[PDB]
Image 1 (cartoon, rainbow, N blue to C red):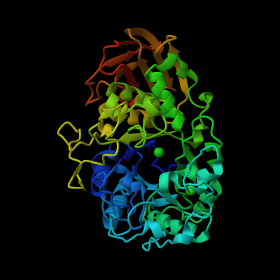
Image 2: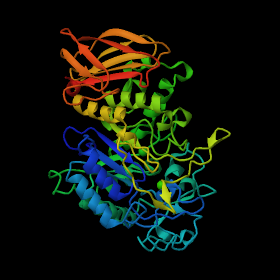
Image 3: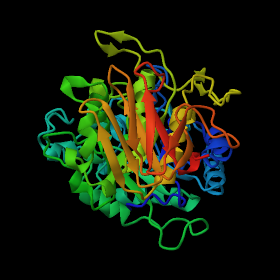
Image 4: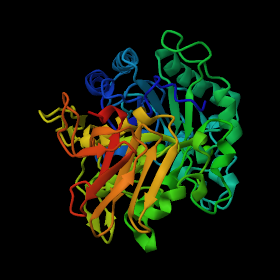
Length: 496
Ligand SMILES: [Ca+2]
Ligand SMILES: [Cl-]
């Protein structure tokens, strides 16, 4: 469960949030595979409630109506096609599995679903699965509202409705079996793993019982005995009765303290400084590295919808975001997930974005295609952070230094730090309000290296900054606080 099942040498996955299956298939072949990306986390592929008030919000996809592979992203044939083409190129697909609940209990009965399936929340009827009143925790929940009212009671957090969402009775074999049927369908199609949505709202033991029903990965692409990669979304900051360690026996867990603390440090909130990142990782109270799925932002906290709050860095904070992603991608702790989003009309009112519900770029509800510009950036409002040179090059940096130890740490006692990864890579950051100019020990073999943040290595030459490492491994670095990107990164494969 703990191994990503990525191709040897690929160390990150990217969340292609709300992308269509045909767009992902093309991206796998034209960019992800050649650029060395390990895999793609896709949006929930199962049928969901079509919500028109507000107009097709991104969160309607977290309200299942059935397990049919029929959504705004495409149909079952398009999904299968995408998994096949991506696998044939070495890029894995990870499915966002929404198995804790069905749709909101107050949603109107009818066929307002992405596949026309009929459902009736009020009477607990979802014929397309099928599920009935007997398959929900209505009688198990002990709160007066039937919803989760207090997170200090670990029992209601698991048996009651997360903000009205009908809660599946995951202790029942029938329900466990319907969910396994769905997941095994995806596994046999070729998916390498899953993100278990709302894992905090499920009992570790119920989750385990489901995973015990799962097939090994498709033997046409994966070695015999391969188990699906499992990462559970569990928001565990401080002081809750539920701990993310309770879920270590099922697979990895999302470490939400990672992006929250990286955000406060890089923003320099409340006296925090980059020099404190010396012992980043478990030393900061994070889960063990081999059980961590890390990221700077995710789809639900980049819009103020989740763990981290206002400290979270996103593409909106382009300069600081690149630096945070760079640090994450250079640092050995955990398995990294890169975010890929779409722009929406942010509208802050009283400190809150009232347009945080807006779904993906679309035409009358039909998701727009991802168009690629001549400079490799995307159009149609897709941000495509995974295509930003600084980010894309750091994804490669992580691949090149995979397995190398964390060494040669340097810091000025403030916000100017540097460190290397064995003798395969070196990275330098300047987040102080003054310039950095110093000769550092890089642990790298002598030679001329291209800085992969400012440029690229293109046919025996660098398009950006060049760094010269001496016989003793020392090298001079100059970064002004006015630089577009206040950090420099060089590695074995950017060497001239
Ligand atoms: Ca639950
Ligand atoms: Cl997540």
